[PDB]
Image (cartoon, coloured by chain):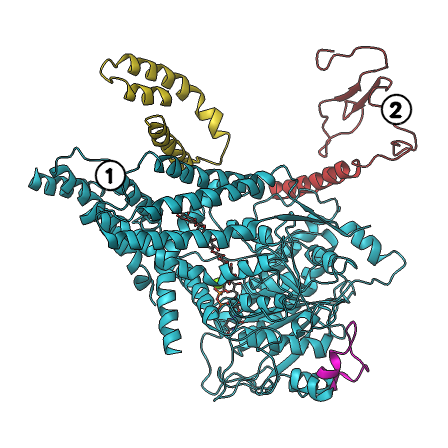
Chain colours: A cyan, B red, C yellow
Amino acid sequence: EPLSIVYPIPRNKLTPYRAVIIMRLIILGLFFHYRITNPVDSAFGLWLTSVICEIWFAFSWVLDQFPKWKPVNRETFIERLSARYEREGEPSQLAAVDFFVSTVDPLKEPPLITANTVLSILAVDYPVDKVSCYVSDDGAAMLTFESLVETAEFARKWVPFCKKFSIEPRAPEFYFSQKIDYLKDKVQPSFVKERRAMKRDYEEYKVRVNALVAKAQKTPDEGWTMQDGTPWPGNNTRDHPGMIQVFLGNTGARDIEGNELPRLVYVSREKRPGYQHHKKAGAENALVRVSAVLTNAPYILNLDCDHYVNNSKAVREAMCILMDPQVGRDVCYVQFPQRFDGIDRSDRYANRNIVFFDVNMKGLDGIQGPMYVGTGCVFNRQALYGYGPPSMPRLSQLSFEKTFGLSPVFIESTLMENGGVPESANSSTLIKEAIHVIGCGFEEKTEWGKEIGWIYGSVTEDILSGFKMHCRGWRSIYCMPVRPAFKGSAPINLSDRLHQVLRWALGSVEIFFSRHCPFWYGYGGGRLKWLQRLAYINTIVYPFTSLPLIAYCTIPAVCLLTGKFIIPTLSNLASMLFLGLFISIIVTAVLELRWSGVSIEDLWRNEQFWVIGGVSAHLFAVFQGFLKMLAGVKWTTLLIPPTTLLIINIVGVVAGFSDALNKGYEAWGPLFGKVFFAFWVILHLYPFLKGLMGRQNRTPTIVVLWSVLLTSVFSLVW
Amino acid sequence: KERRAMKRDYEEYKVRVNALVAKAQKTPDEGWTMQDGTPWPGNNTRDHPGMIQVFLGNTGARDIEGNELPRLVYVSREKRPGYQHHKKAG
Amino acid sequence: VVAGFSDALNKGYEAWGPLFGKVFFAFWVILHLYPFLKGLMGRQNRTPTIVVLWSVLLTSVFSLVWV
Ligand SMILES: OC[C@H]1O[C@@H](O[C@H]2[C@H](O)[C@@H](O)[C@H](O[C@H]3[C@H](O)[C@@H](O)[C@H](O[C@H]4[C@H](O)[C@@H](O)[C@H](O[C@H]5[C@H](O)[C@@H](O)[C@H](O)O[C@@H]5CO)O[C@@H]4CO)O[C@@H]3CO)O[C@@H]2CO)[C@H](O)[C@@H](O)[C@@H]1O
Ligand SMILES: O=c1ccn([C@@H]2O[C@H](COP(=O)(O)OP(=O)(O)O[C@H]3O[C@H](CO)[C@@H](O)[C@H](O)[C@H]3O)[C@@H](O)[C@H]2O)c(=O)[nH]1
Ligand SMILES: [Mg+2]
């Protein structure tokens, strides 16, 4: 019996989708041929720009549509996994999972959300002897350490309450603050009595965390001192010896009933002046090394502080694909879509970004698998080390020493076929080794960052890290449980959203000019599907499509102002080509909507969000990347380019009416073509540039100004 | 003071009703059996002898204070194969 | 109705008003059964795409038949 079944599109919604895109190519090819024939539109310069710019979009669509070829849907069952592995005979044979939570500063991001995430991690519906949790704080702060201690104390009450009543979500902050009737399917007789006590307990706990957070607002002049009566080892944010501690472990705090709980490990890296420490890749690599020595597990799950587990069966759902003997043989990681809560019904800023996850990720899952996003991925431990998929021909102590590190325990740790303490040494030695294997200069002669684990370099290291793992023949899987199984927080204000988009664009640009560029990287040895390298090419060259986009957004104003002629008037042959072009985009979207399940509105918003993203963030990102590449922004500054097009288009397009109207006003329709084409650009970036800022909500009664002054300058001309 | 206790009791009752509903999702192979230790008279949806019972009547359960409550009568019609039974009018 | 306009525009477009009458009759019909019949499909309004879907259908038909 198969643990998971992978079925493609049911063939009723697939062939039409393939047949429309394949037809669109021929229509585009014929459309391009017709334009190239015409050599003149009263301005050779505009003709050169428009044809070149339009050609770029066609390649972008080609690089963007083929990856969506052959979408694949997957279904997973947990009962068979439990029946096959849990076994009434016992013991369970389920694989271990390690959770990584990364933090940087307690003040910038509240620790309550981090504490709620940690509580969610420990409540997974998985054997307690298997799952483990790791929390990493780049900036050693007493608030984070104390918050975990408080979180561990409250975990004694929270865990048994969650397990006995099987409540979901298991994060108290995101569970109690829910208006869904909590008495929906509960059958236990004493659910209400325990729930009322738990809600009282959580509120008391929430107060303690707030007191702890507010306490640390002022820093004592001498420095932080632990309760035992010793200084906190890290008193300087830029200098603190590596710290490792174990909380709520097997040998320690137990549950109120008397059971054990998943072990929580608090590890902080060692920072010293004069050394460069990477932001997230370094922390993840340190966690991987620590996890291997402390509790070597065959799978690693990475999560962010904001994100929390929403489905208690996520570990089982993730493990049913990875632990399947047949399909799980070659799987580097299992990607889970990131779903954001606390978002209005009308997602103005397209924060949920369902189009990418519900279209691209599902479509891209058909070739090899999705791309690493940064969270909700169950990485195979061997895959991170960079060995290569099993059942393949090809991917000494010195080689292991030069490939992994100097610590013999960690070197010997990876030799373990499954995972665990090799010779069950005393905890002190393992702790001492774990403290030693997080040295500041530990990764000096090693390949960490270069070819093993998380990859250093670009800001968006997640894309880079996934690319190298897939380059060695590994596969990834896409999971879409009925429940999200992973939820976090999305940006609320635009300043963070635009910075988020800019940061993604800058990282991709850095990848393009780095050695890890899909154009000339990974060709040697193959093992990468030719149809997936196109997706990587698309994912790395997408920012460059913005420069023609701004040019395409600039042609309507330049033409409509003086030239007023981009293409020759239709010769009774372009009408069908233009008609075929416009209809082609509509039909493909419907079929893509038909099988993907996304809503048309989100597609319009995503299409309406791509245009604004390209003009503003990518243009600066490409120029900044080009400037940085040559060398080796504010919310106000980021909005400068898009405003320029908004002003130029609106003044240009409207001025076209005035100058054209003062003219014979009989040779119009080209005005409509340029006006409508100008409307195309403005309508794409009008709702955001206006909506994203606006004053309060549309209805300003200020739109009359354009009518008057343009009717007044018209009156000045009329 | 009474309202808080009443809300707690109603929540407990709702939990009990939800448990009772969820328990009945899977029917036993032999058939439903009453608490006293006898089979439920109607084991077939299309065949069940007519049943009548009285709960919370004048002679029965009384209020906490000591007063009486309106009588409740649960009646299930008799259905047998080979006859046409109307949905609501009958 | 949208076809009517098209043909009505290709015609002499001078003896109209009967065109207005038929348009108003079709509009009385359409306004009555458009809200419930279409609003059931979509969240609040697919105007984001419906208007452009309908608008291009007019110009596209206005052009193709005009050829
Ligand atoms: O990368 C690291 C980072 O990724 C995050 O996920 C990102 C993802 O990486 C991005 O690729 C994605 O951006 C895609 C947009 O969603 C997508 O809509 C758009 O594709 C455009 C395309 O550029 C455009 O040419 C074409 O549209 C047509 C127009 O409508 C027409 O007007 C014009 O004439 O012709 C074109 C084509 O013929 O197709 C679409 C629609 O505009 O751009 C990207 C496509 O790859 O955003 C994601 C946001 O999450 C991830 O979340 C992070 O965790 C990670 O760090
Ligand atoms: O030196 C650091 C600084 C921050 N973090 C944390 O690791 C993640 C890095 O995120 P960051 O680069 O600071 O920007 P964010 O906007 O918080 O996160 C973006 O980048 C993540 C992947 O790196 C994505 O999961 C998010 O959706 C995306 O919003 C966050 O949890 C941070 O708190 C570190 O691990 N090391
Ligand atoms: Mg963020």
Ligand 1 is within 8 Å of the C-beta of the residue at disc 1: no
Considering the whole magenta stretch, tell me its main secondary structure: loop
- Nearest to the observer: residue A257 or residue A461: A461
Residue A518 % position (x, y): 53, 66
> Which residue is the site of mark 1?
A670
Q: Which mark is residue B41?
A: 2
Neighbour tally class for label 1: few under 14, some 14-19, many 20 plus, Cα within 10 Å: some
At label 1, the amino acid type is Pro
The segment highlighted magenta reads A410-430
Rendered residue at 27%/46% (across/down): A566
* Secondary element at tag 2: loop
Task: Say left or right for C57 vs A340.
Answer: left
Task: Say left or right for C31 vs A537.
Answer: left
Question: Does any portion of residue A432 appear in the rendered image?
Answer: no
Neighbour tally class for label 2: few under 14, some 14-19, many 20 plus, Cα within 10 Å: some
Q: How many marks on residues?
A: 2
Q: Quadrant of residue A486?
A: bottom right
Query: Magenta segment: does it hold A428?
Result: yes
Rendered residue at 48%/72% (across/down): A458
Question: Does any portion of residue C40 appear in the rendered image?
Answer: yes
> What chain does mark 2 sit on?
B
Rendered residue at 35%/57% (across/down): A548
- Nearest to the observer: residue A612 or residue A269: A612
Quadrant in the picture for the C terminus of chain A: top left
Q: Which mark is residue A588?
A: none
Residue A512 % position (x, y): 47, 68
At label 2, the amino acid type is Pro
- Nearest to the observer: residue A182 or residue B44: B44
Query: Magenta segment: does it hold A556?
Result: no
Residue A9 % position (x, y): 64, 43
> What chain does mark 1 sit on?
A
